[PDB]
Structure formats: C-alpha cells, structure tokens
Image (cartoon, rainbow, N blue to C red; front, side, top):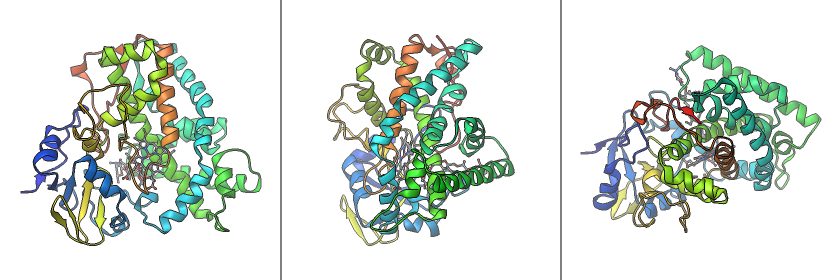
Length: 393
Ligand SMILES: CC[C@H]1OC(=O)/C=C/[C@H](C)[C@@H](O[C@@H]2O[C@H](C)C[C@H](N(C)C)[C@H]2O)[C@@H](C)C[C@@H](C)C(=O)/C=C/C=C/[C@@H]1CO[C@@H]1O[C@H](C)[C@@H](O)[C@@H](OC)[C@H]1OC
Ligand code: HEM
C-alpha cells in the first residue's frame, strides 16, 4: 500500500514516471524507504514549497528518529538538523560573514582554479576523466579559497575531503583518520585567524557578532566543516551532471557556445531540471496534525518533500520536461526553500557558471569518449551522477 521508494533509477538522471502520476492522482502519498520509517511523499511544487516553508514542519526530531533514507548509516547534525530559534541564531552569524558579495569575490579564483584543472587534463591527453580531474577538484579547492586554507595546504585538504564523498571506497578507519585530520587542521586555522585575522571566511566568522552574540569555538569548527561537506559533493555532482548534459545534448552546447552570456540562466534551468537527489529533501516532521490536499499528516509523522519532482511539476513550469536555457520565470526549489534554503547557493551559482564557462572556452568540442550506454553511474544512493566521465576534445 505504501510504494517502495526511491522511484528514481540511479543509473541516469531520468525523473521517475511515478512522480508525474502521483502529482496527478495522489499528490500526498505513502512510501516505504529501504531504511527508516514509512513516510508521506509530497510531489507538487506548491505543496513541496508549502512544507519546506511552514513553521509546523521541523527538522529537530531528525536527531531522535529513524529517518526514511537510502543507506544503512545515518548522517546527523549540522544546521540542517536544527530548528528556530537555535537554527536562526547560527544562521544569522554565518550569513553575516558568508555574504553574496563574498561569494561573487571568488569568481576570479574559481576561474583560475578551473583553468589549472583543465591544464592538468590537457597535460595527460585524451581521454581524461572529467569527474576525477575536474568535478571532484573544483569545489573543494574553491571551499579552500573561501575558508582561507593556505595554497600550500590545498592538496592535503583536498585529499582528506575526498574521503567524505558518498562515492569514496575507503574503509571506516581510513575515513575516520581523514576526518580527524580535517577537524584538527580546521580548529588550528580558526585559532590562527582569531589572533591574526585576514580577509577569508574563517576570519569573518570569528569576528561575526549579532547583538553581542558570537560563535563559540566548537560552533566555528562545526560550521566550517559543515560548509565543506554541504558544499563539496553537491557541487561536484552537479558539475558532472551539467557537463554530461552539455556533451549529450548538442543544442544545449551550441546555445552556450554561441552566447556564453546565457550561462547564468542555463545554470538555473539545469538546476531546476536535473533531479539531482536519489530521493527527497531531508525528512520534515509534523509538530501537529496538518491537512494537505485533504490528507491529514498526524503530529510526529515524517514528510519527504521532493524538490526533484516539484521542479518538474507541469503546473508550475510550462512544458516542464523541456530544458529551456532562457526559461523565465524560473522560481525553482533546486536550492531548497524556507529557513534551510541553501546557505551556499550564491557561491554554488558562481562555481557552476565558472565550470561551464571555462570548459566551454577551453574545450569547445568536449564530448564523451565512450558511448553513453557504457557510462558508470554512482551507486552511493544519495545523489545521482556518473562515476567517471571520460572525455575527448
Ligand atoms: C551527499 C551529501 C552528504 O554526503 C553524505 O551524507 C555522506 C555519507 C557518507 C557515505 C558516510 O560515509 C560512510 O559511513 C559508513 C559508516 C561507512 C561507509 N563505508 C566505509 C563503507 C562510508 O562511505 C558518512 C558517515 C561520512 C562522514 C565523513 C560524514 O559525516 C559525511 C558528511 C557529508 C554529508 C554530505 C552533505 O550533506 C550535508 O549533511 C549534513 C549532515 C547537513 O547538516 C547539511 O550540511 C550542513 C547537508 O547538506 C545540505
Ligand atoms: C550545486 C550545489 C548545491 C546544491 C544543488 C545545493 C542544494 C541545497 C539544498 C536543496 C539545501 C536544502 C536542503 C533541505 O532543505 O533539506 C541546501 C542546504 C545547505 N547548503 Fe547547499 N547546495 C549546493 C551547494 C552548497 C555550497 C557550495 C554550500 C556552502 C559553501 C552549501 C551549503 C549549505 C548549507 C550550510 C545548508 C543547510 C542550510 C540550513 O539548514 O540552514 N551548499 N543546499
């Protein structure tokens, strides 16, 4: 009676047909995930937005509940596990430091890094793996620039970070050692910056004040590592998926080569269209009974709000399955909605823009150097994207 979930096949970016059916016949329905409790699934744009934006739907129970999910282990904590007012306080301090202006200031360093990565690929000759050499490299290096990790330390910081990716095949202790190295280093960097501040985010986070409040020592550290993990795999996977789409849809590539000024709009349309998640936004828990589409979600029940399906809802987006780089309006939920809206979105936007700009300017003939049907797709079961993208140019 509840349907087995996820519906998405991980071996591709296709939106499961089941979503559209439910948007039409059963917009609030029951699902059984591979791990964790049965939950409600909400699929219409208006309802998904309503859930992520409604005060009666909270994240705190995540910490004491068996969350609907695709993997046996549970990754808990961070800002996304918090509710106002505690969430509000931490978020006000972070954004006071992590401004859209800071994000934009990073575009020139993001481009320089992107050029380096493309040099390194040209150096080893076609076919190069776009995933290993570029997509897994650009976002963690940009996070290094953002935080203020000295250039000398970018390689070891990148090495430790790759062990946090859901696609890493390392043992538990290997991952554990990489995490303790990342924590110790970050705590030390924070301590330097406190007693000798520079222009980087760690310095600004240390000095951030809000009506006499400040971030504690532990807060600073947990927030810095939280930015890394929230900002690495997401961006890496979306770069891979966007270039995969550029390489397999000639009209998309051609539109952006003829008119690179369309890249920012194409980044929005692709963020809308790509159902990047295997499943949904982090479960929200009802704090009281809430009636939605005339179904009563009872207090305490978990609710999985699919931004993947919402972004492809025909009721909100004309001809929703079409990728249209000029689409307007495009009020997609690809960076979420409500108090947990992606804190890093201006910088993600910068990176994704830069990735496409540099790749298209350096390698305008970039294309797959194996057939599409032979691509290997990640089975990490959190996000969808290719494990390797061998490319020729
Ligand atoms: C795909 C996106 C997420 O990836 C993840 O959720 C990463 C999960 C990986 C797969 C985990 O590693 C696995 O642990 C198992 C116990 C063993 C397994 N192997 C060895 C067989 C191993 O692969 C976790 C436990 C790895 C550790 C280092 C970790 O805590 C990772 C955190 C990364 C979270 C990533 C980012 O999501 C962010 O999660 C936070 C909990 C939220 O607060 C928020 O960030 C502030 C969120 O992004 C919106
Ligand atoms: C293309 C890349 C990215 C995508 C598609 C993405 C998407 C998201 C989405 C959908 C959420 C809301 C999740 C939910 O409500 O369950 C979120 C939250 C968050 N993101 Fe991102 N994100 C990206 C990149 C980044 C970057 C680069 C950073 C930081 C540098 C970042 C930091 C965060 C943090 C800290 C949160 C939790 C915010 C909160 O709970 O208050 N993200 N992101």
